[PDB]
């Protein structure tokens, strides 16, 4: 039984990668674009972009290990470990061509190491709405003059004693609604039905734990990236960020400038963190146009 | 009924102040010293210091409004509002003479306004283990290279939709053990028996809610103190801070220097946030010695 409805012309399928059964949704023809979701979500956050992209590209949207319908990783949750699974999954479908990569939220954390270590495999890169794990994340404030801050959940989720799972179990829908809307400008896009679907998915006990294990590995990912960042990214890159309440604003592009030689950025006014849902039409257009400057169907 | 055992020779009593029934524990003879507890605790955190102080002073340890056995405040939870209750309580027992003040954690927030507005009523002051509410609190990090940060709970507790009460209700004993131990160096002093006592108190639904209303008023307290701090404190002051895991370190004294003309500070090695319990012998000695420089019984 699918956790989320599959768009017409797409298939929901599974591939074993290093002994981990990964779920993905795939459609289209042409060069490969892999879309990687982030926290609180699944492949389904891309369901509006996928049919438009599928007119020119083969599109694959995996569930991150442990989330959606993907099995947990058997190595670990650090960015370098998870990126192996995503890199090998992409290469099963694009072994002879470089592929495009689009990532949101912790999808960035889980793809950056394989981008930097396999640059010849990455044709074009789109990153939206999350820091690459590095020391900049230690500058975000715990509290603001307007109330709760943007990433205090970094501490909540990384805490031991299974603090987050223990407090959120039995309240998964409640917490996810608060978390989404606290990081949104446009909350009306999150219907009760949509919130129900996302809540049911990450409330699976192994998915609730998987969600926070990404954050419990965050400092390890920072330490990994300190070495990897000695090599700058050379492929064409675009960053997107929300300019409204909940968004990263100018931080996204300014951080990427330290990582990539060839980068352009957009801040979307009136949009928060959840760009594919809050601001689907402009986000879709910017991604499609940026990727279509390359060779496509 | 008594939530915590009263030391021999002390009395547990109540005093109505501006329509709010405040619980306190009182003993000894001589000039008055008021000891004000902080978050996660009650008057009982002072129970090892109180018999020693009571040999030289009249000692009163109130429960903060809404916490322990004290009724919630009727005005509000900002520092200036709550300080009225504590000032009037102290002056009921010391109407013609200045009194001493010792405060820990949010006890600082709830006493600073009455200290600065009634300086002639405060003979000597001891503050430990919390920032005075001001703009400095906006500079603490949400996340650190070691894991959860010191004050990410500011955002958690201040969050709207009763986020904190909704997640923590029914799990108060689990949450308080995690919160206390994660802020401690000498965690071994928090036996299951002691944690049971503290958790049963703040699990009262009005006490769980009161606990977080102090943080929901924090930005208001910051705004209040921006005006009040135009006058420095003139009385002898001492700050204490833990030097170990969970402690404020050098911040406590460095902030206090902006507030007080006459301040000495100590950082206690191997001690975290919970000085009366983690480091009873050195903390009690420092407090008794400092207060005994003034006239006593």
Image (spheres, coloured by chain):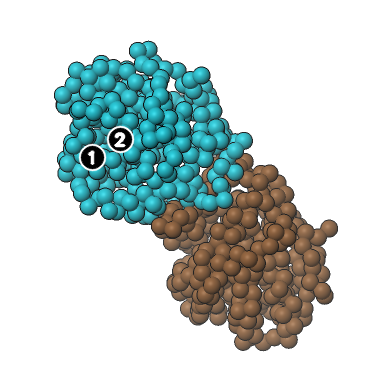
Chain colours: A cyan, B brown
Quadrant position of the C terminus of chain B in the picture: bottom right
In the depicted view, which residue is nearer to us: A84 or B240?
Answer: A84
In the depicted view, which residue is nearer to us: B223 or A163?
Answer: A163
> Same chain, marks 2 and 1?
yes
Q: List the residue tagged with mark 1.
A: A118
Q: Residue at x 39, y 46 (%)?
A: A78
Secondary-structure class at tag 2? helix
When asked about the image quadrant of residue B292, the answer is bottom right
Q: Is residue B255 left or right of residue B192?
A: left
List the single residue furthest toward the front. Answer: A19
Q: List the residue tagged with mark 2.
A: A87
Q: Residue at x 45, y 18 (%)?
A: A5
Q: In which chain is the residue bearing label 2?
A: A
Q: Taking B190 as reference, is A259 above or below it?
A: above
Q: Is residue B33 left or right of residue A251?
A: right
Circles 2 and 1: CB distance less than 8 Å?
Answer: yes
Residue A96 x %, y %: 20, 27
Q: Is residue A185 visible?
A: no
When asked about the image quadrant of residue B46, the answer is bottom right
- What is the tally of numbered marks visible in this picture? 2
Q: Is residue A122 visible?
A: yes
In the depicted view, which residue is nearer to us: B235 or A179?
Answer: A179
**Disc number placed over residue B100 in the picture, else none:** none
Residue A294 x %, y %: 16, 26
Q: Residue at x 70, y 46 (%)?
A: B205
């Amino acid at each position: 039984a699918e956790e989320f409805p599959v768009p017409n012309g797409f298939e929901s399928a599974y591939r074993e990668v290093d002994g981990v059964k990964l779920h993905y949704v795939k459609g289209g023809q042409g060069p490969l674009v892999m879309l990687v979701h982030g926290f609180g979500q699944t492949w389904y956050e891309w369901h509006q972009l996928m049919p438009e992209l599928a007119k020119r590209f083969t599109v694959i949207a995996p569930d991150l290990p442990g989330l959606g319908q993907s099995e947990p990783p058997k190595t670990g949750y650090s960015g370098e470990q998870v990126a192996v699974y995503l890199h090998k999954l992409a290469r099963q479908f694009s072994p002879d061509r470089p592929f495009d990569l689009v990532a949101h939220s912790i999808g960035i954390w889980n793809t950056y190491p394989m981008v930097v270590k396999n640059q010849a495999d990455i044709a074009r890169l789109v990153y939206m709405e999350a820091p690459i794990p590095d020391a900049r994340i230690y500058r975000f404030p715990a509290f603001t003059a307007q109330g709760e801050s943007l990433v205090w959940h970094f501490s909540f989720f990384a805490a031991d004693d299974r603090l987050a799972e223990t407090l959120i179990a039995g309240k998964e829908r409640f917490f996810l609604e608060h978390f989404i809307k606290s990081h949104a400008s446009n909350t009306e896009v999150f219907s009760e039905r949509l919130l129900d679907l996302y809540a049911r998915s990450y409330a699976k006990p192994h998915s609730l734990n998987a969600s926070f294990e990404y954050y419990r590995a965050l400092n390890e990912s920072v330490r990994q990236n300190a070495e990897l960042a000695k090599t700058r990214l050379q492929m064409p890159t675009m960053t997107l960020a929300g300019g409204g309440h909940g968004g990263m604003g100018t931080f996204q592009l300014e951080q990427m400038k330290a990582y990539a030689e060839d980068v352009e950025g957009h801040v979307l006014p009136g949009c928060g963190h959840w760009l594919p849902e809050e601001c689907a039409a402009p986000m879709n257009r910017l991604v499609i146009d940026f990727l279509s400057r390359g060779r496509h169907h």
